Image: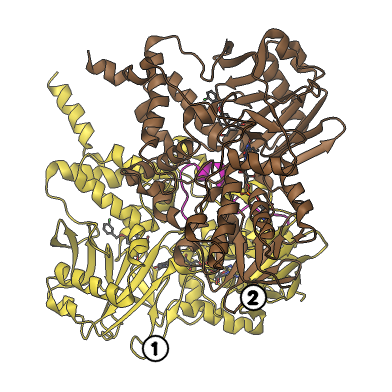
Chain colours: A yellow, B brown
Amino acid sequence: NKCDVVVVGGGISGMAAAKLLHDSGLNVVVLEARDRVGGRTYTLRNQKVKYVDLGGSYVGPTQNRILRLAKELGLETYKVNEVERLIHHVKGKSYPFRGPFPPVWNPITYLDHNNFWRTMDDMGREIPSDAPWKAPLAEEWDNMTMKELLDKLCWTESAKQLATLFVNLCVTAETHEVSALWFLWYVKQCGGTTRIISTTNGGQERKFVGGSGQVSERIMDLLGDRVKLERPVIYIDQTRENVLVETLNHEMYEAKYVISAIPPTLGMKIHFNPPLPMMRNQMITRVPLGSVIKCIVYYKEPFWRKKDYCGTMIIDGEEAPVAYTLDDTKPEGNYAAIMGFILAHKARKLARLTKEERLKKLCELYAKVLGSLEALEPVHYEEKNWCEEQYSGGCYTTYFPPGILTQYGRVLRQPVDRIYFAGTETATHWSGYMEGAVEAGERAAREILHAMGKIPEDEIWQSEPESVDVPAQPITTTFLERHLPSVPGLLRLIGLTTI
Amino acid sequence: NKCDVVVVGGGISGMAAAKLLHDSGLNVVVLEARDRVGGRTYTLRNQKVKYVDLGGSYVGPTQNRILRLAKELGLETYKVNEVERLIHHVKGKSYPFRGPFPPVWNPITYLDHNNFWRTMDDMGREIPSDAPWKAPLAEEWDNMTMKELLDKLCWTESAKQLATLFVNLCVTAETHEVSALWFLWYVKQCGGTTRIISTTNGGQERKFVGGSGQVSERIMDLLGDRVKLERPVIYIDQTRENVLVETLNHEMYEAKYVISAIPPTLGMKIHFNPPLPMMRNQMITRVPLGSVIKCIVYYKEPFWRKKDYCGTMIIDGEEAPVAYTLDDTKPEGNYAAIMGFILAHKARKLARLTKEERLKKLCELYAKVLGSLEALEPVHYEEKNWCEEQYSGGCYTTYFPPGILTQYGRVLRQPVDRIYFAGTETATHWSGYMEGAVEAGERAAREILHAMGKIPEDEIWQSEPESVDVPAQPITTTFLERHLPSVPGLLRLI
Ligand SMILES: *Cc1cc2c(cc1C)nc1c(=O)[nH]c(=O)nc-1n2C[C@H](O)[C@H](O)[C@H](O)COP(=O)(O)OP(=O)(O)OC[C@H]1O[C@@H](n2cnc3c(N)ncnc32)[C@H](O)[C@@H]1O
Ligand SMILES: *Cc1cc2c(cc1C)nc1c(=O)[nH]c(=O)nc-1n2C[C@H](O)[C@H](O)[C@H](O)COP(=O)(O)OP(=O)(O)OC[C@H]1O[C@@H](n2cnc3c(N)ncnc32)[C@H](O)[C@@H]1O
Ligand SMILES: O=Cc1cc(=O)oc2cc(OCc3cccc(Cl)c3)ccc12
Ligand SMILES: O=Cc1cc(=O)oc2cc(OCc3cccc(Cl)c3)ccc12
């Protein structure tokens, strides 16, 4: 029954909030809908795989809150394999390379590719991380999809195809589904295009030894029986002196404050008394999650490394079930594996198949991309379709369709009386990631500490010291990258010399 | 506890289904979240207005099922006032007109406007009513917003501004929010642009004497104690012999079958066991409802009639709170009033104001458009902001953002085990309206009758005889409307 704060949701955000609150001396309870903690992180263990992350997995430089939280829990990271060459597979052929971006040789195409990435970042710098709706052209940008933006910007099909794969991979949604403003904010708040797509020096640099699901489990250990499993919240009543939170299995909890640490749309699964204010009531029906199947095929050895491929494949084409892969081999070099994502519409289309049918398509694709018959001999397969999860709604995160962020975005983390809002969707730095979950959980716990009169207002938002274990190389550009014209810029230059 | 069918929701659709099954001899229960029936219909009564519809109100020709149902309940309709001239207010001046569409005088603008309305209807002819995802260009049209379509189509700002108002009024959403495929389907399954926008011989022809809220009320009267108010469903368990339906107030119902008669996205408020299949699980997070404030300003007399204006106003531009009005005067000529809609982003923007502030902005606008100081002296005001309703989500109806219809649309009315889907969103003719609520409720009730072996499969979908009281006249076009070129068509001749 009685405590100081009820946290709804026991993913990384809810658990980080509850930890911070418990450490400050408050009585907290965490109500978790599932028979497990971790939410969109989930570490499967069995004898065949040892452990494997089926949800959120990668961490990297500039993600200093999840690194510090995980380090304090006694966790360690290891580097994702990028020793050998990456592959870009396009129009049925593979092209090995080094560096974060596939190289482009054709000079006109090079200008178009260079201008594409440069412009994403140019536009992003006009967008405040904490208030994207305050960008000067916020309305214009929000009223366009990413497909429309790409249509205006990309003068070559080569750039437009790569850019489409970029969007599908970043937000598990089609370019026609998402707001240009939202997507430009999303990339910028992770530190830009280079940071977001990079393995070395970027978001996919590292994984946690033993799995990311340990973060949530270890905090559950510290909190003990304050974590209540299989307590889906159905009802929040704020009409009396203390808040009442009711669960599906018939229990009632009384609290001074509530943290909602669930994806924004899952807020719909709760009946509110009094009803939510209008802006929030409608916002929660306008913010879906993307569609992805995360698939892991195991092999006897990491045979790709022998042909000088690191296991990274960027695979363009409608026939390809998987558009992106990484080496998922253990740091000890055993349980050789390839992780791949089935993205957006393909997750919907391929969900119709059996597990065995999907394994077969993946192996056939990998054999072709890697030019290797060994890829047709899996020893094991694990997969997870996040579209089927009642208590997630999708993965990795919430996307904004056109027109939504400028109209409703300002209420995302606005308190509703004594309900405060956590979850990765409400973060301002790596929103959508385990990193943003930690930022949002800890910020919402501090909003409650400030309301209780325990901390001053200036301590609600707190900087994080850089990790000493995972240093961040700065993002740099060359002089030519900076000053080379776009395609229409060069055309304008030609019309000027000719006139 | 125990019955044959539990219907979740007591709006028109859920009540229609329950009535059909009751009349068949089955034992029905209706679980309704609110302290009232009607849902997105709501008739307020007080001495100042007598009665007023603050949600769904209008009915018209080709809406035969709502007309039959209401007649059986003892209801009568009357005609919305369209005797005098309509007004199109553009660039700060009023231009009175007759006929459904505002006239265009510039020859280039004329061609552009003509082409727009014509093209909406041509594109709709390729969209099947019962399967819009089967349109030959479904993906291409689904992957574009209506804003993109209008930018391509409309060569003048005049046409683009009227087209925009059209979208905003029809679906209470912005052009950039909505799929082109879904919008074009929506228009097509109402019978086309003329039918949808017309008062005479269209959707706004008539209203119910005493209010549309009487439809649900009178069915509730007929169902006895089978309707349970303040029973929001929170849980549906299908793992056993009988379906188990649990309510927020701790009650438990057991039935052979369930009809879900609530907006698709409101299905999010129910915890399901076993979980819903993947496609429906994601579909119900992808389908918002629009945003509207319905506002009624009352006057001593319908003074506009003295100036040969009927009270219909089509008001262009960003600055105007209301883009569209109709005369809301009672048949007897008393309780004079103007009904107006504050639409889409204006509902969001103006909601922060007080009721009295919105009243003043409305009266000043109507004074300017009607050219009458009489509009400045209202006797009463009523309004309803539908965006604030927990158990509606919005009004009038669900819209589909780009990409959604083709990817998810086929699961909208696919049964989940022993759960069948009603609600106006599931209709194939006047979906979004009271008419479509009836169609979908009665169809869902018959799917279950068929599941019980009571009727054959060919009796699940049933045609409706035309109303004798509200007969439909055909929509016609002229030779020039059909054959005049578009702007780029005239350019190609030059
Ligand atoms: C799914 C996924 C995610 C993911 C990704 C790949 C996939 C396939 N890769 C990532 C990566 O490599 N690196 C990274 O940093 N993030 C990655 N992502 C996203 C990441 O997993 C998420 O950003 C993060 O896990 C989100 O955390 P958050 O704490 O904000 O949210 P949650 O995990 O969804 O947890 C919410 C909890 O709430 C419970 N719930 C839901 N409804 C209720 C009710 N009504 N009552 C009580 N509890 C409720 C959920 O069960 C959950 O535990
Ligand atoms: C709001 C509105 C609607 C409207 C319109 C103008 C406005 C401002 N103009 C219309 C018009 O002139 N002519 C017309 O035919 N339609 C017009 N519309 C739309 C029309 O009202 C709707 O299409 C129709 O009313 C929809 O009926 P339906 O029965 O399909 O849906 P509903 O009214 O929303 O009823 C659903 C009921 O379900 C209850 N509910 C919701 N959740 C639960 C749970 N969990 N448990 C139990 N009950 C639940 C609702 O409270 C509601 O009663
Ligand atoms: O955003 C999340 C994310 C999770 C992930 O596992 O891999 C990514 C890989 C990305 O980029 C890989 C890449 C490299 C070169 C070109 C292109 Cl288009 C993409 C971008 C985001 C991600
Ligand atoms: O769709 C619902 C709807 C409810 C209504 O009350 O009035 C309408 C009026 C409409 O058209 C009026 C109109 C006339 C002439 C031009 C334009 Cl753009 C609009 C269209 C839909 C509606």
Evaluate whether label 2 is on the same chain as label 1. yes
Q: Quadrant of residue B316?
A: top right
Q: Which quadrant of the rendered structure holds the C terminus of chain A?
A: top left
Depth check: give the residue in front, A128 or B255.
B255
Residue hosting label 1: A46
Depth check: give the residue in front, A32 or B182.
B182
Residue A409 within the segment the image draws in magenta: yes
Q: Is mark 2 within 8 Å of ligand 1?
A: yes
Q: Could you tell me which secondary element the residue under label 2 belongs to?
A: loop
Give the vertical position of A229 relative to A149 (above or below).
below
Number of residues whose C-alpha sits closer than 10 Å to that of mark 1, classed few (under 14), some (14–19) or many (20 or more): few
Which stretch is magenta? A398-417
At 37% from the left and 22% from the top, the residue drawn is B115
Residue hosting label 2: A231
Q: Is residue A196 visible?
A: no
Depth check: give the residue in front, A407 or B398.
B398
